[PDB]
Length: 226
Length: 224
Ligand SMILES: O=C1CC(=O)N([C@@H]2O[C@H](COP(=O)(O)O)[C@@H](O)[C@H]2O)C(=O)N1
Ligand SMILES: O=C1CC(=O)N([C@@H]2O[C@H](COP(=O)(O)O)[C@@H](O)[C@H]2O)C(=O)N1
Image (cartoon, rainbow over all chains, first blue to last red; front, side, top):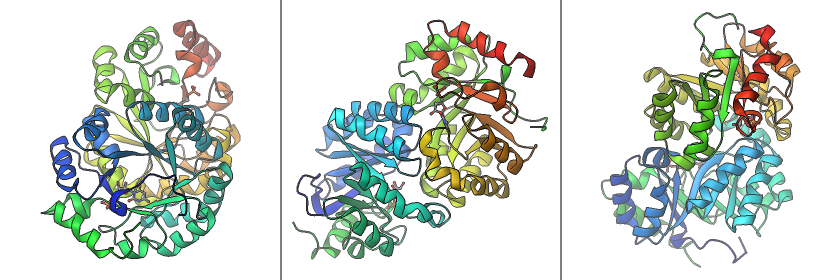
């Protein structure tokens, strides 16, 4: 990405905090705070500890929050979900593109009004993505561009797909990518196209999360700056 | 549907309780309880009041709860979402099929392991559904059949699509359909294929929710 008006992710590493217990979640996040300042919080944690967990993370840690809720409902419900989520302190929210343009627009409008951001998930990192998602991936990405979407989520496990997504969305867009580590994606190859990588279990399940985070960062030192 | 062991939804009417305040949500639900015993609780309410709200609905009104979370993540995450959801008193959970068979199977395994139900959302009711979901709907339904899914969600706004979906899933499957009221779906044509209809705003935003529910039931009395 060439734009400077994007969230500045420390070390280009976003922690996918999917532990389902407040104690383990707060412990691991705290132990890696030195390397990460942007945390992706999803339903595994939220449905287990509640939305206030978002406020607490910003309190204890001075981190940005990406609510990975893969919003995928009708326009009316999507609007409500985004409103509740931003009200709770989320800086950005991840939204699915497959439900259509109106569903995505609903999220974009709320984000616009509240001054927050929407990240469009154009395709996924798991095996199942090949069944229905990849066939529509190109068009979903193009729909995002036409809608004026500037933030995207693409698969680390499929660098060949990530290259294509980047070409479609352009350099004036921001791209983050999950699937690194546990799913087999490589941090370095992924950062050839993505602006930041998302890492979950490789860090939060490690005997030493801090060392795991440090190791990943060391492995991409040549791609770290700016 | 022709199956005898299907979910028994009173008056074939499911309340989509999408109000975002526990007071209005609980009050309106109580107001229509004599007409509805099955409530669909989604993220608008859950993200606003917390997951404990599900048990509250059960304790207060003894209604069955369908957690409409449109689960649409990778298998591993879907697993966690379903587990947390069934631990909250949800009798069932709605999952997306677009992410593929592994994502759906993950939900099915948890439901089976925790003795609850999974509803597979095939085609959606809004206009945008025509862009990508509609073209994959029949295949998603067939995937559901092959996986052993017995509960489905289809659009009331497109009865002709609902008819095709019913053909694919068979009569031994349970089908619920949203889109009645606010979205212009016709209850009559919808119930020709769906076992139960989902109604939200046409009821919870009505000056008199009870009267609203009553009216809906009156318009489909011949199907009850
Ligand atoms: O295509 C995608 C989207 C997504 O957000 N995710 C999420 O990214 C995280 C990956 O975590 P992990 O590093 O495999 O443990 C989880 O929170 C997933 O739900 C993914 O793995 N693939
Ligand atoms: O295709 C679909 C799926 C679905 O769950 N829904 C949900 O069904 C409800 C419909 O509410 P309403 O009657 O339009 O106010 C909402 O909670 C929606 O999120 C839908 O409208 N269409």
